[PDB]
Image (tube, coloured by chain):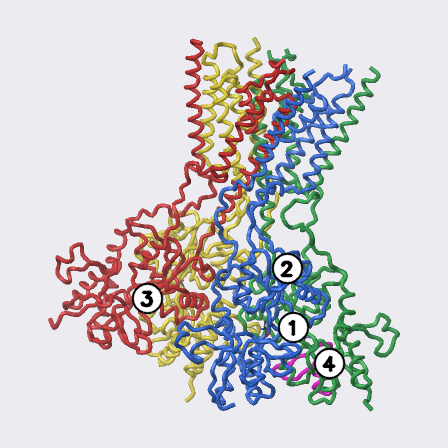
Chain colours: A yellow, B red, C blue, D green
C-alpha cells in the first residue's frame, strides 16, 4: 500500500546548502536551499513521499565514450537508484530522448567569468600621456621652422653683416628659451623680427596652459581599464586561456555549433595544448583567481551572480551572456511519477512561488554594495615612479654634456 | 489538392516585405521575406497549397477587457477566419490555451534601443570657449591704453627728454611681452611708469590664472559624462522616457509580473503621461529618431539587432536581454495538419535551414560599417584636432613677416 | 440621526480633490474621498446613507474668545447643523471642550516652508575670495619687510658707499617685480642679497600655486547654502517676516505657549504689523512665491510634503518638525455615531489600511522625484561680471598715473 | 494602612540617578531625578506613603513570543509584584491591554545618534603633502649635480679661463633662479652649457606643473565629500552600522511596521551579525564612542538631547524624528489609584509643574553650545594656518641674512 521514492540532488551552493548539523542528519533534514524547498513545495502539492539524496557520482559527469552510457546522476534514474531528479541540469533533446523532463522552472544562459581588474604598475614614461603623441612632432617641426624664419629675417640685409648678434645658433637658443619660459638675453630690434617673436609666445602660453589643465583633470576620477568587451575579443586574442567545465553541455553545444566564431573557438579548444577543462566549480574559481585573469572560465550566469555576492568581490561579469536555456525536473521513461510532478511544477510556474524562492536564495543574499562605490577613496601623494622618467633624462643629458667639452678641447689641441 | 490554406501575415522586415513592384505581381508573389520562404518550405514538406492574407487590423492582438474577446490574428484564429498563422508570434500561456504551437524554432529576449548620442567634433577655435567674445574684446581695447599712457608719460620736457628709449613702438613692444610674462629687455625708470607696469602685471596675474582654472574645470566636468547602462538607471532616471508597443504581450508580461524592477517599470508606464505606448513598430522607431535622445524604446532583441545594422545605423542596443521567449507556428485548436506541420518544423530544424534562411537575410543586409565600435574609450587622450587652430595662427604669423621684411628691404634700398 | 448623515468635509488636495466634471457630478461621486469611506466601515455596518458634504465656511473653523462663537466645521457641529466630521483637523483640548474625538489616525506636526534659494549675481570684487582678508593683509607687510631688509643689507659700507643701484625705491621696485613673476634686470650680486632673493621666490611660487589650485576647485562644485535652519534663527530674524495661518488652531497654540523662545516668537507675532497672517493655503503659497526674499510661511508637514512634489518644484522644507499632534475624527459630544466609529478607526489601524491611505496620494504622486549631481549643464564661459573688478582697478590706476607727472613737472619748473 | 506601597523604577539619567553618597545615605533620599522628584507630587495628591524599589532585571521587558510570558517592569505589573511604576515607558496597545495608563504627560521622538566627525586640524607644513618626501629629497641632489657640472664645463680652458663669469658661486646662483622660473642676469655661452640649461629647464617645467595639478586634485576630491544627511540613507548605506536597544519599543516597531524602507531596515537588523542589539544605553553609548565613524545608534530624541549636551560633547543628533510617542504612569488593571493618578497628572499638567521639574533637569545641565555663528569656516576660504609655515620660513630667511653682513663687516673692519 505505502510507497516511497528516492530523489537525486547536488550540493550546489545557490541551490543546496549543508546545514551545520551535518554529522548525523538525514538528507530530508541535512539540507536547505532552492532545490530543497522546491522539492518540499512539490511534495506539498503532489503528496508523494520521498527522501532526499545527493547524486551518488557527486558530479554531472560525462557520457561514456563511444557508448553514451549515462553518468551517475542520470544512471541513478535509469538504473533504479532514484526515480526523480531535481537539480540544475540543462534541458536538451539528447537527454529528453532517454528520460522525460518537466516544464522548465527557470531560463538562463552561459556567461564568461573573469577576475576583477586592478591598477597596473605605472609606466616609466607615462608622464607624457596627457598630451598625445603627434603633437610632440608638430612642436618639434614648429620649433625648427620658427628658428629658421627668425634667423633669416634677422640677417636678410637689415642694413648688414655684424649689425646684431642673431646668429643661427643663437637663434635656435632664443627659440628654445622662449618656450620653457626662461630668461631672454636679447631681443629683435627690427619690426619683422618682433613680429616673429610675438606669436611664438601666444603659442607656448596656450600649449602649456592646456597641458597643465588636462593633467589636473586626469588625477580626478580615474575610471580606467576594461580589458575585454566580450568573448569576441577572447576569440581574436590567444594569450588569455579559457575553457569550459568538463562534461558540461556547453562542450556538446560547441561540438556541433556552426557559428563561425563559436566553431573557431571549439576547434581551438579541441586543439588547445594544456588542460583547459575543470571538473568542479571550486577548480574553475581557483584557476581564474590564481591566473590573475590570464585564464577565464565559462559557466551558467546564475552561478556567477551568486559568487559575485560572496565576498571577496574580485570577480565580475562581462559580455551580454551567450545563450538562453531552461532548467527543469527530470524523470525516467515510463515512470508514473512524471505527470503528477509535472502538473505541480506547472502549478508553481503559474502561482509564482518560484519568485519567492528566487528572492529567498539570491536577492536577500546580496551584500556587495561596493559596486556603486558606497565609500569614497582619498587621493595620495605622487610616487617617485610617477615622475621617474625625468631623472634619467637629466643625468643622461649631463653625461653627454661632458663629452662635448673633451672633444672640443681635442679639436682645439692643435 | 483539397483547398488552398489560408495564411495570416503582417508586413514586417525582414519577416515579410512588399516586393519592389508588388502591384505588378501575383497576390502571393507580391510579398517577400523570411517567412514567405518558410511558407514555401511548409508547402513543399506538407504537400499542399497556401493562400497569403494580410491580417486585417495589423496586429497580433490581445484579450479584450471585460469581454474576453480576441482580436488581431488570434481573433482570426479563434473565430475560424483562417487556417494557419505565419508571423513572429511569441508563445505565452494566455494564448497557448486556445491555439496550438509547433516545437519552437527560435529563441529571443527583449531589448532596449536608443539613438546614437552625438558626433562631437570640436570647433576650429573652441580652445577660446572659456572666455567668451566680450572678454577678449575688452582685453584688446585695454591693451592700447597702457601703451598710450606709457608713451605720453615717458616723453615730456624735463623742465634731457632724449634720455630714455620709450618711443611709441618700444612702448608697444614692452607691453605685449609684459602681458605674456616673457620678460623684457628694458624697464621703466620714472615713478609714473612703474605704477602702470604694476597694474598691468596685476591684470595679467588675474587673467591667466582665471583662464587656466576655467579650462581645468571644464575638462573635469566633461570626464563625468557617466552614460546610462544596463537599464538599471531606469529604476531612478526619469529625464529619459520609454515605452512599448501596444497590444503586444510584452505589455501583459509587464502588467502581470511582480519583480520589483519590472514592477517599478510597469508602475511608471501605468502612470506616466502622455501615453508612452505606440501602435506600430515603424512609427515607434521613428519616435526615437524624432525624440533624438529623450525617448527610448523596448522591443524584441531580434528586431533591435536587425534594425541597428540597417543603412541609417543611427541607433543601437543598450543592455542585455531582459528575459527569454520563442516563436512557434500557430494554428486553430485541433487542426489536424498541425502535427504534419510540427514534423516539417522538426525536419527543417534538423536540416539546418533555419540557419540557411537567416544567413541569407541578416548578414548581407549588414550594410553599416560598424565603425567606432567603442574599443578605445578615448583613453583620456587629448586629440591633436582640439588644438589645431593655433598652428594655423603660428604659420600665418611667420608667413606675414617675410612680406614685411621684403617691403622693409624695398624701403631701405631707396630711403 | 434620521438614518441619514451629512459628513463634514473640506476640499483640500492632500485629502479631497474635485473631479473634473464638478458641473454635473453630485454627491460623493463628485469626489474620491477614500480618506473617509474606509472610516465609514461603521457606516457600512449601520447602512445609513452618507454624503461627503463641503464644510459650510470652507475652512477648518475656529472658536472665538469672549463670545466663544464656534465657526465653520466647529460651529455646524456644535449648533447641530452637522453631525459627523471626518475632516483632517487638529486634536486639541480647546476643541475637546465641546466635542469629542476618535483615536487619531496619523501623527504630524508644525513645519516651515520657504521659496527654494537661487544663485545671486556675482560680487564685484569676488575675485579676491580664495585667499581671504588675513592673508591678503599679511602679504603687504611681508613685501614691506622684504624690501626693507634687501635695502639694508645691500647698502652696508663697501670698501665708496652706493656702489650699486639698490636704492630704497629700486628695492621696492625689484621686490614687487619679483612677486609678480616679471623680468627684473638688476641683480643683487651679493651673498646676503642673493639669500634674501631666494626665499622671496619660493614664497611667491607657493602662494600663486595655492591660489590657482583653490580657484580651480572652486569652479568645479557649487552649493547654495540655506540662510537659516532653526527657530533660534527666526528669533534672531533680520527682515524675513513669518506668521501662522489665520483662524488656525496653531495660532491659539502659540498664544498658549509659554516657553521662552516660542513666547518671544509669539510676542513678536503679536507686535508685528497687520497682514502678517494668511487665511488660506493658496494665499500662503502665493505670498511665499511673491516673497522672493521677504517672507516665510508655516504649515503642517503633511501639506508641505504634498506641495513639495508638485509643480513648480521651487519650494523646500527647512528645519525639523516643531511639535507633534494627531489628526482624527471629530463629533459632537457623546454621539451615538461618534462612539462606534472609533471601533472602525481602531480595527482599520489593525488592518493597516493607513499605508494604502498614505501611498494612494503622497507616494503615487511622487512626480518631481530625486535630483542629484549626476550630469550638469556645461560650465560655459566665464561671464564679464566674474572679473569686472580688475578693469575698474586698471583704468583707475591709469587715470591716476598722469597726475604724478604734472606735479613733477611743476616741481621742476624752477 | 497602605502597607508602605512599593514603587518600581529603573536607573537612568536624568529620570532617576543614584546619590553620590548612596553608600551611606538611607531612604528615598538616596536618589535624584525627574521621576523620583515627581513622586513627591504623586504623594502630595494621593496622601500616601511609598518606598522606591529597583526593577530586578533592569529592563522594560517583552512578550517573549512563542511563550507569551511577560517579564521586566511589565512582568512585575502583571504578576502583582509592582504596585505602581514610574519610568519612561511609552504607551502602546500591546501594553495597554496588560496595564492601565494615565493621560500622556510628555511627547517624544525616536532619533539616530552618531559620533562627532573629528576636526581637520591643519599641519604646520602640510602644504608639502602633495609631493612626497623622496621627491623633495632627490631634487636637492639633482640641483647640486647640475650646478657642479655647469661649473666644471664652464671653466675648463676654452683652448684663457678669464673669458667668462661662471664662477662656482655664480654657477650655484644661476641654477637656483632657473629652477624658480624667475629668470636670470646672464646666459651660458658654450654649446655644452646651453644643453645643460635646456635639460634643467625641461626638468623644472615638468615638476612645477605636476605639483600644481596634484594640489588642485587634492582640494577637488575634498570638496565633494557630501556627508550623510538626515541619515535616512542608512536604509541605503551599508558601510556604517547602527544599533538598537534590546526589548525596547523600537524592537517591536521595526518588526511591526511594514513600510518598505523600514522593511529593509528590519531585514538588515535581522540579518546583520554581530547583532545590532544592546542591553544598556550606557554600554551602547560606549560602543558608539569606541566604534567611531562606522557605528550609530537609535534612541529616544529626548535622551539624545540630554546626552549630547554633556561635557564630552562628542555625540549629537542627526536627522529628524522618526515618529511621535508619549509616556504615561502605569499600574495594574482596575487599580483604584489609577483615576486619582490621572487627576494628579491632569492637575500638574495644567499647573505647568511639568516645566517646573523639567527646567532643573536639562537647562542647567547643558554645557556645550559651540557652533558656527556670525561667520562660517566651511564656505570656501583658506585659513591663514593652512599656509602658515611659509611665513616662518620667510621670516627666518630674512633673519639669517643680517648675520652674513655682520661677519662681512667683522672681516673687512680689520683689513
Ligand atoms: N552541468 C550543467 C551545466 C553545464 C554547462 O554549462 O554546459 C549541465 O550540463 O546541465
Ligand atoms: N508582439 C510581441 C512583442 C514585440 C516586441 O515588444 O518587440 C508580443 O506579443 O509580446
Ligand atoms: N489644521 C489646523 C488649522 C491650521 C493651523 O492650525 O494653522 C486645525 O485643525 O485647526
Ligand atoms: N521607554 C521606551 C523605549 C523605546 C525604545 O527605545 O524602543 C519604551 O517604553 O519601550
Cα separation, mark 2 vs mark 4, equals 35 Å
Task: Name the disc covering residue C229, or none.
Answer: 2
Give the side of residue D108 with respect to residue A24, left or right. Answer: right
Cα separation, mark 4 vs mark 1, equals 23 Å
Foreground of the two, C34 or B110:
C34
Name the magenta segment's main secondary structure: loop
Tell me: is circle 2 under 8 Å from ligand 3. no
> In the rendered image of this protein, does residue B198 appear above or below residue D388?
above
Instruction: Determine which residue is flagged by label 4.
Output: D345
Q: Can residue D82 be seen at all in this image of the molecule?
A: no
Q: Can residue A213 be seen at all in this image of the molecule?
A: yes
Callout 1 secondary element: helix
Report the span colored magenta: D55-80
> In the rendered image of this protein, does residue C341 appear above or below residue B20?
below
Query: For the residue carrying disc 2, how many other residues have a C-alpha within 10 Å: few (<14), some (14-19), or many (20+)?
Result: few
Foreground tag (3 vs 4): 4
To the question of a shared chain for discs 1 and 3, the answer is: no
- Which residue: 60% across, 18% down? B156
Cα separation, mark 1 vs mark 3, equals 57 Å
To the question of a shared chain for discs 2 and 4, the answer is: no
Q: Which chain does the numbered disc 4 sit on?
A: D
Give the side of residue A79 with respect to residue A190, left or right. Answer: left
Amino acid at each position: 500500500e505505502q510507497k516511497t521514492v528516492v530523489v537525486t540532488t547536488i550540493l550546489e551552493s545557490p541551490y543546496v546548502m549543508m546545514k551545520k548539523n551535518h554529522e548525523m542528519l538525514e538528507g530530508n533534514e541535512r539540507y536547505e536551499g532552492y532545490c530543497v524547498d522546491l522539492a518540499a513545495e512539490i511534495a506539498k502539492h503532489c503528496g508523494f513521499k520521498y527522501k532526499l539524496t545527493i547524486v551518488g557520482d557527486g558530479k554531472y559527469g560525462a557520457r561514456d565514450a563511444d557508448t553514451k552510457i549515462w553518468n551517475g546522476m542520470v544512471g541513478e534514474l535509469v538504473y533504479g537508484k532514484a526515480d526523480i531528479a531535481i537539480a540544475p541540469l540543462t534541458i536538451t533533446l539528447v537527454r529528453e530522448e532517454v528520460i522525460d523532463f518537466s516544464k522548465p522552472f527557470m531560463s538562463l544562459g552561459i556567461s564568461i567569468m573573469i577576475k576583477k581588474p586592478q591598477k597596473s604598475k605605472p609606466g616609466v614614461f607615462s608622464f607624457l600621456d596627457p598630451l598625445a603623441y603627434e603633437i610632440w612632432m608638430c612642436i618639434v617641426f614648429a620649433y625648427i621652422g620658427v628658428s629658421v624664419v627668425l634667423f633669416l629675417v634677422s640677417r636678410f640685409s637689415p642694413y648688414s653683416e655684424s649689425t646684431n648678434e642673431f646668429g643661427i645658433f643663437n637663434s635656435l637658443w632664443f627659440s628654445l628659451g622662449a618656450f620653457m619660459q626662461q630668461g631672454c638675453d636679447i631681443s629683435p630690434r627690427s619690426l619683422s623680427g618682433r613680429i616673429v617673436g610675438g606669436v611664438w609666445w601666444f603659442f607656448t602660453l596656450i600649449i602649456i596652459s592646456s597641458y597643465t589643465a588636462n593633467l589636473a583633470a586626469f588625477l580626478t576620477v580615474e575610471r580606467m581599464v576594461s580589458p575585454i568587451e566580450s568573448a569576441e575579443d577572447l576569440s581574436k586574442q590567444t594569450e588569455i586561456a579559457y575553457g569550459t567545465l568538463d562534461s558540461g553541455s556547453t562542450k556538446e553545444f560547441f561540438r556541433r555549433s556552426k557559428i563561425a566564431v563559436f566553431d573557431k573557438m571549439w576547434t581551438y579548444m579541441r586543439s588547445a595544448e594544456p588542460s583547459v577543462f575543470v571538473r568542479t566549480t571550486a577548480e574553475g574559481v581557483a584557476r581564474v583567481r590564481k591566473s590573475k585573469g590570464k585564464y577565464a572560465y565559462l559557466l551558467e550566469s546564475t552561478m556567477n551572480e551568486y559568487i559575485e555576492q560572496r565576498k571577496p568581490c574580485d570577480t565580475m561579469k562581462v559580455g551580454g551572456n551567450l545563450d538562453s536555456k531552461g532548467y527543469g525536473i527530470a524523470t525516467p521513461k515510463g515512470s508514473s511519477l512524471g505527470t503528477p510532478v509535472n502538473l505541480a511544477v506547472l502549478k508553481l510556474s503559474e502561482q509564482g512561488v518560484l519568485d519567492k524562492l528566487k528572492n529567498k536564495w539570491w536577492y536577500d543574499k546580496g551584500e556587495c554594495g561596493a559596486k556603486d562605490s558606497g565609500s569614497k577613496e582619498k587621493t595620495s601623494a605622487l610616487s617617485l615612479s610617477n615622475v621617474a622618467g625625468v631623472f634619467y633624462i637629466l643625468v643622461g643629458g649631463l653625461g653627454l654634456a661632458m663629452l662635448v667639452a673633451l672633444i672640443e678641447f681635442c679639436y682645439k689641441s692643435r
